[PDB]
Length: 157
Length: 157
Ligand SMILES: COc1cc(Cc2cnc(N)nc2N)cc(OC)c1OC
Ligand SMILES: COc1cc(Cc2cnc(N)nc2N)cc(OC)c1OC
Image 1: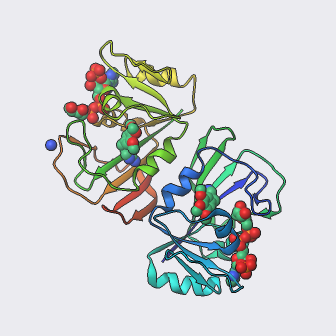
Image 2: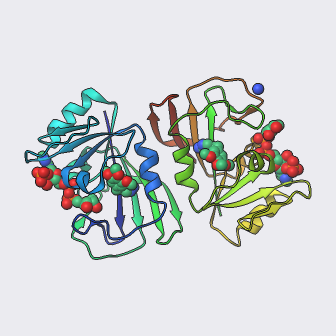
Image 3: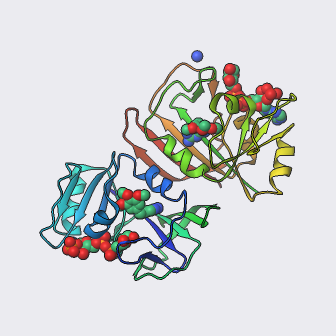
């Protein structure tokens, strides 16, 4: 199965200040809605709880705890390893859609990054990992909004 | 300024049966909405009338008549050269968003294509031109829907 990764980070690499995103870049989330439509996503438990489920997406949620989910559209996995083995029988394609921890543990398995950088440098204590130079930008487009943002697609070369 | 082009075509190349699109693929238009967000779009006058202005988007519309719009978000030009010269004072980027005529006229200026191919072969007045080998696919993603669709980004090689 193909592993993609989709994130939005500030220019200082912040993705998270506790359970919040410390910015609202009007329009950016349309990109996430476009590329996740009828896809399978892999999310950490904290990101899943803070951001909720959208319709027309399936979720693999990883926890080390006894946490569970009423949603029929969700499968809980005890590890990333297990989620990958599971997903591989359920889909051609999974989009890793966050957690700091999840991004750190999955970035090496990804063949395509969808990265949005927001024109702000806010307070924060979760950070996107460093992008290995095995990856190259193949597409980029700037957006003007309340806070500008840059969308880039990276492929593993 | 960089010229992109964004289109959605059936597998047989149909983009239009008169002023309608002969199909509705749930999900696909999210990609159009996310990539045109707060961008300048170049549209022919026929497409503009049949499909209407969207909010949060700027329009360069070309006519060979004295046709005009009812919208301070719209600039009418008598030619594509005039539209380009005018836009270049306002923006580093324009997305050509159709007409069959417009696509044919502008494909030679475009350095990035955003092409959605819908899994259907309907009847069609209007067709997307053939993609010259001057361009190469740099990204691709498949979507399952009521009608499946494939999204590809082509760059000028
Ligand atoms: C996993 O849950 C969501 C996460 C995000 C964050 C996010 C926002 N933008 C981009 N490009 N990638 C992301 N991962 C955004 C969301 O909706 C806009 C989510 O709703 C399901
Ligand atoms: C020119 O305005 C629109 C055009 C289209 C057709 C279209 C649909 N999908 C893609 N990817 N590109 C397109 N050009 C679709 C639209 O709405 C979903 C438009 O907004 C009114």
